[PDB]
Amino acid sequence: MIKEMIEDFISKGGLIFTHSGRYTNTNNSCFIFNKNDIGVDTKVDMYTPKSAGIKNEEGENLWQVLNKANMFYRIYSGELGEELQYLLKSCCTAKEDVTTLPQIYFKNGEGYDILVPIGNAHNLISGTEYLWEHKYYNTFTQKLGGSNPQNCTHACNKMRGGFKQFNCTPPQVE
Amino acid sequence: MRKFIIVKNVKVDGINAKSSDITVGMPPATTFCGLGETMSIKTGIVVKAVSYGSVKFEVRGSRFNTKPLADGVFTLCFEVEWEDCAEVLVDKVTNFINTARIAGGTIASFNKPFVKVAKDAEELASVKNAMMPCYVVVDCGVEVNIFEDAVNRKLQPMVNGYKKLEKIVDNKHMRDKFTPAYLATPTYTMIGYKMVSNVDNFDQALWQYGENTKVKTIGGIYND
């Protein structure tokens, strides 16, 4: 069932991540998986070249399946058991890439850190679903991945309608 | 809480309105904290905190049909430590603003900087009102999360810092190979806007860096 999905995913160079710099630049290949971030409703994103992934008859590819019925937590925790685990976590692996990303200094005591900001898959995927369900429209919509999102991430490849952003316009002195 | 320099009507063109993947509009308090911190570095002046307010602001294309760029006008107020003079401060600040940037956009003009002083809480309200008119940013905290809070409290999310995710291993492309570098992702708080004069305690509008890679106000979460 799920195995052939993951099987075919590991076949291609498949990565599961919670954070990525792709969201800010389609050529960046930074992918990070924050293990503490994972919970019952944690939405995740994935990458294969050309966003492949076999399409189980139900019509769904692995990204769709993993994010439907909290299927990622279930599998990642163990109500699935060894087999449909550890090789799910075989792809939850990092990939450092700084190119095209910003570098900022952020004060820290006497001294500074330098931070390379990358974006969060859950806030994009789950965020957009949540503002959709609750009829919240004080937003901008942003389509990611360029024309050709299928080569950016799996969520970009399927959420072609775009991701919701908070409209942070302030009030004006009239 | 003694000395403050105020710069009214800083007009800024071509602001990069995108402060995170999910926030487009007003530049977050990190940005203005970074402005003051940058001023401190270049001018040698000690900057304690910064209050900033909105006067005008518009994301391009959001009022009329014509990466997300904006333009607006802000009023700034820096809490400062300085006793060498009064206009030698005003000149060092003028000199820095003329070429500073705010979220990537260029300053086009500003009123002349001026200095205000507070000896107690009551004079502090005079510093506050000298910013009028503008809508300053105050910290309302997160109750549940920014999504639920945005729907239910009808408040506005704002980048307030970063969570370090991993240390960067090979500094090949890093600008600076000595400062500790981290892959990081923004953290948020919820903010509200107040016509400055309506702010009870000015400490609650004065933003500065804090522990664990966040900014916050001197006086904490805003309360009426």
Image (cartoon, coloured by chain):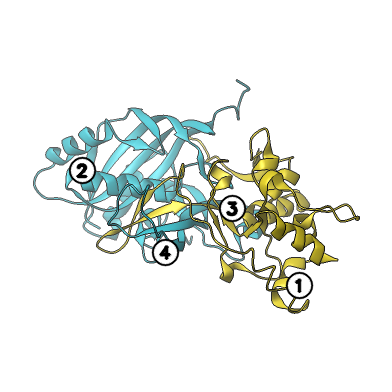
Chain colours: A yellow, B cyan
Discs 4, 1 touching: Cβ within 8 Å: no
Q: CA distance from mark 1 to mark 2?
A: 56 Å
Percent from the top left, x then y, of residue B144? 62, 66
Q: Relative to residue B87, is residue B3 depicted above or below? A: below
Q: CA distance from mark 3 to mark 1?
A: 42 Å
SS category of the residue bearing label 4: loop
Disc 4 and disc 2 on one polypeptide chain: yes
Residue B28, visible in the rendered structure: yes
- Residue under label 1, please give it: A84
Q: CA distance from mark 4 to mark 3?
A: 17 Å
Viewer-nearest of labels 3 and 1? 1
Q: How many marks?
A: 4
| Neighbourhood count class around disc 1 (C-alpha, 10 Å): few under 14, some 14–19, many 20 upward | some
Residue extending farthest to the top is B66
- Residue under label 4, please give it: B220
Q: Using the rendered view, name the quadrant where residue B35 is placed.
A: top left
Percent from the top left, x then y, of residue A131? 71, 51
Disc 4 and disc 3 on one polypeptide chain: yes
Q: Relative to residue B17, is residue B109 depicted above or below? A: above
The amino acid type, in three-letter code, at marker 4 is Gly
- Residue under label 2, please give it: B42
Q: Using the rendered view, name the quadrant where residue A120 is placed.
A: bottom right
Viewer-nearest of labels 4 and 1? 1
Residue visible at 21% across and 57% down in the picture: B119
Residue visible at 42% across and 50% down in the picture: B29
Q: CA distance from mark 3 to mark 2?
A: 35 Å
Nearest the eye: B47 or B117: B47
The amino acid type, in three-letter code, at marker 2 is Lys
